[PDB]
Image (cartoon, helix red, strand yellow):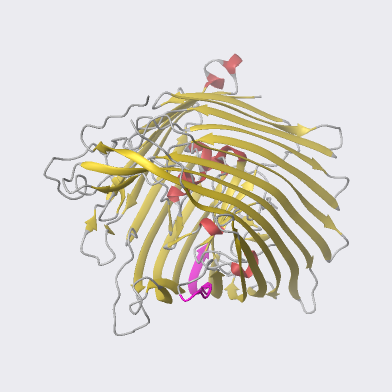
Amino acid sequence: PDSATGPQAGYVAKRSLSGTKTDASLSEIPQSISVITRDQMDAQQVQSVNEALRYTAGVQANTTAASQRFDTLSIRGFDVTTGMLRDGLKGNTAQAWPKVEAYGLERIDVLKGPASVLFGQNSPGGVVNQISKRPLDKPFHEVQIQGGSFDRAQGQFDFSGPLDDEGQFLYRLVGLERDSGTQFDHIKDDKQYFAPSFTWKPNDDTSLTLLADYTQDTFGAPRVFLPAQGTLLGNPNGKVRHNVFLDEPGLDNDRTQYSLGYLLEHRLNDVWSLNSSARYGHVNLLTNTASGMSLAPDLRTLNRAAYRFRIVGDTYSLDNNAQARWNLGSTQMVSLLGIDYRRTREDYYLRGGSASPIDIYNPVHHHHGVFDPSTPFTNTVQRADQVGVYAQQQFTFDEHWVLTVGGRQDRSSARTDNRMNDSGSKQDDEKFTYRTGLVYLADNGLAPYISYSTSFDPVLGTNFYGTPYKPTSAKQSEVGVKYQPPGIDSYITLSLFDLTQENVLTTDPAQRLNKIQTGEINVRGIELEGKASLARGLDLLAALTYNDAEVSKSNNPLEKGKRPTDTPEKMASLWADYTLPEGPLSGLGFGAGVRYIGSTEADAANTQRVPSYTLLDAAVHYDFDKLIPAAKGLRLAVNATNLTDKHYYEGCSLTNCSAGYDRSVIASLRYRW
């Protein structure tokens, strides 16, 4: 076997624990599941989780250029920031979200559709499962340095191997530091990251891995205001520089985070296995901003305001399970029972004040100008206790049919108290979730599945007549066929699905200051997606996505509601990398990819379209080895995003647009021994 976790060459992963909480071939999994191999992440020099999801079907990379604080992305229509996982553990509070330095990962698993079945509360979208780099059993050493666009300068390392002669002791030090500017003025893109790790494996029964890390980054403010009137729409004052800086320079916009955790598997015999994961995770986010409120009557002056807010959150996440592999018939059984705590605390506060308005065309900033961010606003400490019990059984009937069944009970509780006025408030929810799925594994490699699963996310806080909101729910059907070609290293997935979210907060007609749970979002789509690492070291990928989205202000099947904002009908993408294997220029390589994103709708009402766009990507790269043999192990790699520098809008409201990624270059020198 290949590992469901450990490293691998090629673009084509063959198995994952993400879809099933057990070691499973991709065809065995009754959902639709994607694995982004490390290698691919490198042949594209990707630099952030969100950026590496750009070539995945039914997944869309909504984090904007100007504000890079989070890996904000969307699976099958829904934002999945409550769907993020590191090593199968959530590490996120209501407001405290974490950002994982993509260098630190060994692969990304993406499970499309509702998965509360295994992971508890979650967005309808799916789970992004960020699998950490873990201590390797044979030495491996990598240093690389890079430069590139916007005065970029970055250094990093990755060291592994045994400490002893058995491989009873294994380490891994990983580190990266970066000083970069970004296509905009006075916006930095800085990181520092270090992650020690350690695997003690006495024998083959017990295997315990230790996982620490500290990540300190800087980025720009959030809610970058660029007006529509001037970009997408007309403005009588003329077009606006798509990349204008309209906040104030030199304000604190950063965050520390760190975590320590362990992963322990342990065999008991031939049938029983116990499993435990848990991690402490801190996140200390700070933002100072002078963000744009609105454009004054003259369509030229931006009124603004001062804000400071520190969000601090601490996570204790813990997941224990036990697994059994027997046979009653000549029919292989796989059983699974588990428990799943989380406890969180989040320490919030917001402070407001005034901000000199600034001009859209002639921006001007200066200090000794007004910025006073001290009026208390909100101020919180919010504790949660989450617990799930889950189980699931898989049946493999005489080596061909995989039937998969499972469910989860969940308790979610959330004690929020106002330091502003010395009141407490408490919310308490429960839901059963579940999944049914059948797969037939044909001999010719084809493998059709059907399945149904549910999902739920709480809605925190109290409505208007002072009653707590209800959790949102999601149900999904999927037919789909996955494929393994005769004997080539390749994987194609075709999936068709209908996915629906219920109790979506709509604005109440009776009381214009109230939200009622009347709303449906419905999304039916197709996702064709394939990867191959071919015969002679050419790699490949394609991902197509058609999505029918329909917002339903309230259940009425003679409606025909509208598309939601910023959601594409089509998104396709392609990529090939290629290293020359012999002959004169042995070691020289090229890489190209085309990414496509379709029209969106600006306004809830669907009267205003936001331009489609296609972007090209490129790479040359050279391994010295043949040329200077004494420099064996060295690598020059140059990569371009948006090669042709199309200046596009990421998304538009009717108020404002988002500046798309202008052409960016990363060049690097990498050395290995």
Residue 79's spot in the image, x, y percent? 46, 59
Residue 574's spot in the image, x, y percent? 39, 48
Is residue 367 found inside the magenta-colored segment of the image? no
Front in this rendered view, residue 510 or 666: 510
Front in this rendered view, residue 574 or 344: 344
Image quarter where the C terminus lies is top right
Front in this rendered view, residue 444 or 283: 283
- Indicate left or right for 360 with 15 as reference: left
In the rendered image, the vertical position of residue 90 relative to residue 191, given as above or below: below
- Indicate left or right for 268 with 638 as reference: right
Quadrant of the rendered image containing residue 240: top left
Residue 40's spot in the image, x, y percent? 52, 42
Is residue 476 found inside the magenta-colored segment of the image? yes
Q: Which residue lies furthest to the front in this view?
A: 421
Q: How many tags in the picture?
A: 0
- Indicate left or right for 344 with 375 as reference: right
Quadrant of the rendered image containing residue 436: bottom right
* Residue at the image point whose x is 37% and y is 82% from the top: 555
* Residue at the image point whose x is 58% and y is 35% from the top: 216
Magenta stretch, residue numbers: 465-485
Q: Residue furthest left?
A: 236
Residue 107 visible here: yes
Front in this rendered view, residue 210 or 546: 210
Residue 91 visible here: no
Residue 262's spot in the image, x, y percent? 76, 48
